[PDB]
Image 1 (tube, each protein chain N blue to C red):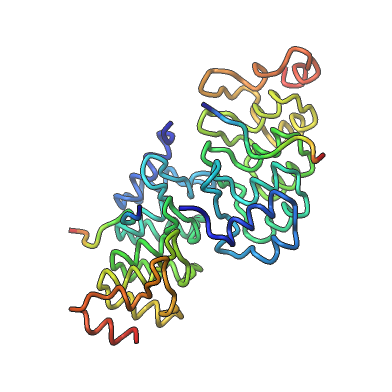
Image 2: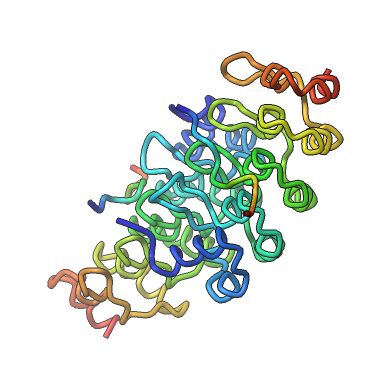
Length: 158
Length: 158
Length: 12
Length: 12
């Protein structure tokens, strides 16, 4: 019905950035477990979204999957980019995260960063080959999602 | 929402043993995609359950996750054992599958093999260190799940 | 509710 | 619809 207590605790520890607890629960079997009671985030999704750098580094070095998709098709790079976590985004890319990956609605990490107003994240993605012309299912590019005030992000993607 | 056309085709090809199509569609990004329309099986779940050895081998060589769990907490080893697929089980074990893993109801691969009367599978899992005393959430061990007719499996476990 | 894994025992 | 990823912008 729910996650095992061990997996629930691992997921919570990833979210909380409690690296000592992560180290005590993380194994090859549990490292990519999924939060069945939420949107099926893995430990890496939680660590990436809540800017838990030490946890992200540990997870990446112990079998965490940069390609794992949650219930909505997001990979942990989407979480990092949506919430502006530059160092985390850098660690994921260094461990082979695919920049042009898309979720169930065909949003890429660049769509997330652009919509959320994260210039340096947008620039980081571009240098690693992020395609600013990719349309999501609506037909919108990352440029299309940029808020009007962000003329610098507009200029970059443009 | 459904899977992409590409992911649907990969999952179908895996189930079918269509290795040529798997070859065309299998990428680092898609190899562990999940069947969100069904029980969230990965390509490796499907290939393992339907005894598609050539596809199992290909997927394992291309980063398929032996620890990935479906909607009910099953790993591909569960699928192989439940359906009596000895070679697939051995391939999964050779590629790092953990024999003592349990699903959301704490059923292990050995519970499956025992219940399904798969004698050779039980022996293999034991030969590889499976724990015959593990109880599932009903309080049942694999031995408890052996049908009374199956006196040889009983004998094997105790 | 617990259901069967994807798969089948016999190829035929 | 499409919901936001797990996470938040600021640790505080």
